[PDB]
Image (cartoon, coloured by chain):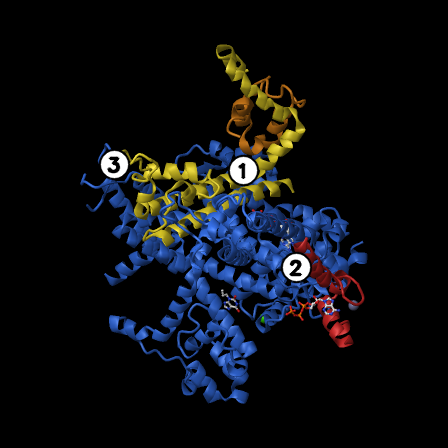
Chain colours: A orange, B blue, C yellow, D red
Amino acid sequence: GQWDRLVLNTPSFPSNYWDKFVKRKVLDKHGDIFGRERIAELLGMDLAS
Amino acid sequence: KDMVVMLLSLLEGNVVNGMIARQMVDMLVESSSNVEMILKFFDMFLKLKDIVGSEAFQDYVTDPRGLISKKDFQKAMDSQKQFTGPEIQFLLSCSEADENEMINFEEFANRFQEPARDIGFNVAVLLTNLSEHVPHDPRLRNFLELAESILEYFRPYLGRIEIMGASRRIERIYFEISETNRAQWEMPQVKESKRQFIFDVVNEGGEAEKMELFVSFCEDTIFEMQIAAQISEPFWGELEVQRVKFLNYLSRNFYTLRFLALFLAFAINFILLFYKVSDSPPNMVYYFLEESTGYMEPALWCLSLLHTLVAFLCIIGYNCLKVPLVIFKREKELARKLEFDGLYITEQPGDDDVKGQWDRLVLNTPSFPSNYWDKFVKRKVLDKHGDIFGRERIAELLGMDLASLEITAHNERKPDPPPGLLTWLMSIDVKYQIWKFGVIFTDNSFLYLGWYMVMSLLGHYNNFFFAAHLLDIAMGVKTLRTILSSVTHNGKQLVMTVGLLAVVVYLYTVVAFNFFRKFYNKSEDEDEPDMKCDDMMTCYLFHMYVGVRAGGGIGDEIEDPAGDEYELYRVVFDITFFFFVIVILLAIIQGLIIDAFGELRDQQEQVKEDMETKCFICGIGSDYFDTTPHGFETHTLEEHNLANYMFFLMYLINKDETEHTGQESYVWKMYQERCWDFFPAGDCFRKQYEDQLS
Amino acid sequence: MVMSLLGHYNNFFFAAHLLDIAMGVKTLRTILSSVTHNGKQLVMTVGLLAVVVYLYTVVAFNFFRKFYNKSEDEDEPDMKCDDMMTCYLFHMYVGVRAGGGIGDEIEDPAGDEYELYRVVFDITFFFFVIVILLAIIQGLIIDAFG
Amino acid sequence: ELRDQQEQVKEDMETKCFICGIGSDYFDTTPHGFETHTLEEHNLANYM
Ligand SMILES: Nc1ncnc2c1ncn2[C@@H]1O[C@H](COP(=O)(O)OP(=O)(O)OP(=O)(O)O)[C@@H](O)[C@H]1O
Ligand SMILES: Nc1ncnc2c1ncn2[C@@H]1O[C@H](COP(=O)(O)OP(=O)(O)OP(=O)(O)O)[C@@H](O)[C@H]1O
Ligand SMILES: CCCn1c(=O)[nH]c(=O)c2[nH]cnc21
Ligand SMILES: [Ca+2]
Ligand SMILES: [Zn+2]
Ligand SMILES: [Zn+2]
């Protein structure tokens, strides 16, 4: 669990796993309570893009 | 809350799809709007409590003093998106904003929580009861959906059980569980005790006394919970408070002290490996350390002192932590025997029961119910058995003052003995203390720790006695306990096998002493002969010592019989010795150990299978429940969880009798009478309402 | 791969790759799994064996030193239990490997004031160490099979 | 073999009635049903 923190911010995270949209799904699920910008920083996401 | 209690009382003894429940649902439907308003009140404030702790809110709150402006609060609410605009306006109105429009969100959140918890819990109980007794009603499912947050919040605190009620019908009971009770239950020691109790009742437990054993386990667990609470941390009085602090610290850190003692013993023996013996100092030999550093002797001295100190502290920690449960259990069983069995009134122990004979001392003692709660057991016994066996006689047996019994009832008297050393000495009850000391010295763990302490003290006299404390690794490690238990399991059989081995060797020795003496010379020098079988005792010692240890038997040691008139007799002798003694008897030992392994394994496997296949309470199999998906899991977690029965017992004990409901009073009276018929056996709510539920 | 590369430096490192037969053969994996199943228990049993041998070594170092001379030449004596470390090594090395225990290796106590003490010492060593603890190992393996 | 013989005897006696052969489950449908059956209803000592 500590090691897996590195790959969260990586663009290539869902490289072998099919779901490429899991980051946006998590942002939708937990953005309101935990902050959209904060989730984006955690997951390497560019809110504008 | 009172009105909801009245409604729940109306629902007492309510069958599935009952008229009263359906009319309650109709009333709720008629009052739907106001019910929704109430649920919205509760959910708004519950959600606010978590939102204000949410960090996102902390992002919006910039002000150092912890206050949040009305505008920033509104922005945070809309960001969370869980609230509507009207709800945010209502929250702002309820906020006690100062003239600067600044709000203290902490107090705003904490204000309505505590007042509304009881009503929230009772509303959840009402809705749960109604849902379970009217399973198919969209009008009720809508209310439940509105109350989802409340039910989620109160889920850990809602305990449900099933009993056989006065109506010959299974009834579900809903009650409240305290967070402290749940935490104390979840403590690891309680879990280990639960595992041990389950293993015992499943491997060597009778179904008839299963519920009595379960109730006793619950009582003991409550007592341990009290002990844990007491020891838990948040000029004679000053000395007393530091003393209790020190004792509580020892009790809390008892196991760490045990591990520390083990580590110290290991270090001491590591050092002891370095001794050497020489005639000269560094006719009578000298034992001296050998080290280049030279710092090792004082280290050993210190380690010995610390080990002894830790042993003494472990004694104290045991006496403070675990002895009280021993005394509580012993007092409880004696009280129950007196009240119900009438042991010392009618039956009288057999004189084969040393414990029953020992317990006579404490009957007449004032301090008898010192650790056990019931202080009135003596008067109860006097009422029960006085007429047949004599009130004065019972009073003499139990140390009771018939006159003072009446005065205690007439009014309270205060004979204030201001605290003093002499007053404490008077308070000491010699007979009770002696009985208690006998109990403790009989306790095995106390004996082991005392042996530990004595061996450390002797180690100070001779440092090599510190090696015995390395045997504590057994008790330290569960794996070692299991391995040793494998041997102990068939230990009596092993001793009998050894005795048989001795007997067979004795017979072989007789045969040798009579017919085969010449072959037992163990001397090469012909002038001086050393005959081991010229005497029977020497021959027996020789056989038992060399032959058993040998792989081929005695024939390996004794002289070749080739070219002798008794050659065939001796080869039979030796081969039979080899086969019977070396092969079989040893093989018997190894097979006993192997069988012990399998027996322990199958015990654990059987316990696990019984717990996974059947309910501990009702005994109904997993198949019936699994007819419904996850049915057995739901049954063992919700319907018939034993933890919930324990929590119910605690809840009844804490609750006032006048507040008791009909179900609670029924179960309480049956518990006091020690009747366990209310426990559902062979029946369940599902089975009873099978057709109505579906 | 590393063992092969080291094998190029010294060809004898290629023997380690014969341990791959385990993973190659399912039967070998099952047999080895029988041991691994109770491996922790086996290690604990070995530790207990070491502890008991240590206790016996203490007893010998205190009371039975004279019996631990392993030299026939009287002029030069080789005493294995004049030091505790040497005595422990001697016990763990010879006694366990022996079938009758340490008594097989050390000198006959006949005609000595401590004869009965030593026969108890040797017989108890034999029964507790050689018979039981080993038997515990074999029973653990047997139980793993079942 | 001897161990499993004893265990099987004990399990058979605890699960089924010596007389009727009906299992403990049917009787335990009623609380303490098997105990009542083996002590009162179908006690072999009473037949003797
Ligand atoms: N009446 C019952 N109440 C509770 N559990 C029951 C009951 N009847 C059977 N069980 C079985 O007991 C199991 C309880 O879990 P278990 O004994 O594994 O302990 P635990 O509290 O979950 O934790 P741990 O495994 O750490 O000890 C349930 O999953 C179920 O299999
Ligand atoms: N028809 C039956 N009659 C009596 N016992 C039966 C019958 N069917 C099964 N049993 C089982 O036999 C048990 C009888 O008890 P058990 O065999 O342990 O001997 P006991 O007379 O109680 O005494 P002890 O254990 O000292 O021999 C009953 O508890 C029940 O488990
Ligand atoms: C551990 C003792 C707790 N307890 C109990 O187990 N049963 C009771 O009837 C009672 N009355 C007050 N305390 C009680
Ligand atoms: Ca009342
Ligand atoms: Zn059940
Ligand atoms: Zn029958």
Callout 2 and callout 1 share a chain? no
Tell me what residue is drawn at x 62 percent, y 33 percent.
Answer: C31
Q: Is mark 3 within 8 Å of ligand 1?
A: no
Report which residue position mark 3 lands on: B290
> Does residue B66 appear to the left or right of B166 in the view shown?
left
Q: CA distance from mark 3 to mark 1?
A: 37 Å
Give the number of the mark in front: 2 or 1.
1
Residue lying at the far top in this picture: please name it. Answer: C8
Secondary structure of residue under mark 3: loop
Report which residue position mark 2 lands on: B617
Q: Residue B12, position in %: x, y?
A: 68, 65
Q: Amino acid at mark 2?
A: Ile
Quarter holding the N terminus of chain B is bottom right
Q: Residue B670, position in %: x, y?
A: 61, 71
Q: Is mark 2 within 8 Å of ligand 5?
A: yes
- Chain under callout 1: C
Secondary structure of residue under mark 2: loop
